[PDB]
Length: 293
Ligand SMILES: O=c1ccn([C@@H]2O[C@H](COP(=O)(O)OP(=O)(O)O)[C@@H](O)[C@H]2O)c(=O)[nH]1
Ligand SMILES: OC[C@H]1O[C@@H](O)[C@H](O)[C@@H](O)[C@H]1O
Ligand SMILES: OC[C@H]1O[C@@H](O)[C@H](O)[C@@H](O)[C@H]1O
Ligand SMILES: [Mn+2]
Image 1 (cartoon, rainbow, N blue to C red):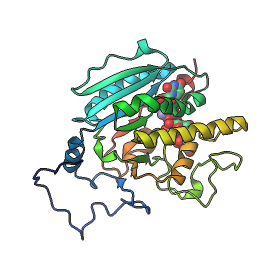
Image 2: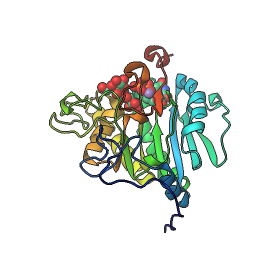
Image 3: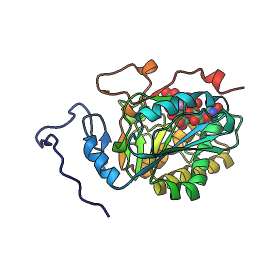
């Protein structure tokens, strides 16, 4: 049950004036595409605070990637869901390496110890199993929504309740202007992740997705099961869990899509005029050095 909103004074939405004319702000299945200028965060904050919403944020910091946690968490404190209840879940093979970050009121952090796999591919792919294992009791009792992100990142601007919905993905910043045949979906029919050249709405990122706990448990269980079928068939998808996530979101359309505001790489892609804000961005790193002992 939802109580009434209070009286609020804010600018009138004008029907014959779009918020953004330069971008698609709604998918063909009527899911909002979240860009700056499309939402009044005061109305959304009211709606979600009246529900006492709790948001879980999952982040994996395995092996050398524990070095990214200090900046990730300190910037999360400045920018992620401030004013709302937040539960961080840090999955790591090194609990003693998790930095002591000071948190705002109504925010908590739990450290979940997990095993480390040797190959970066497996570390990244096995997040789906691990998230689904933890949905299956812990998340269901503790949070309303789960946001599942890469750790090699920092928040630079607001990331708030505008993203929350039963199921969301995020447009990969390398592909948002690309035609679908250029998307790097898995193209081998022998893989569970296979998408034909004439299918596909968007190219979503493996590094930022989420939803209600029920929908995120569905997605992560389905992706884990599909990866297991591929492993048994001796095939590993071209972009690993990202490829499986794209297949899942093609067949189970998300109820919001985040614009590339929400996962950008300024070093590789700069700051185009269509991005009014860069909210969550890649930390530069050396793949070969950071992924291997
Ligand atoms: O040795 C590793 C490799 C990967 N990851 C986790 O897997 C995510 C995806 O890997 P990565 O960020 O290397 O992929 P990229 O964004 O560089 O393509 C990382 O953010 C970490 O959460 C990890 O913790 N340790
Ligand atoms: O083509 C898909 C790939 O795009 C690259 O830019 C990115 O580094 C990869 O992680 C993967 O998403
Ligand atoms: O190579 C697979 C990786 O691709 C990246 O683009 C994505 O942000 C990571 O989360 C992981 O899915
Ligand atoms: Mn990453």
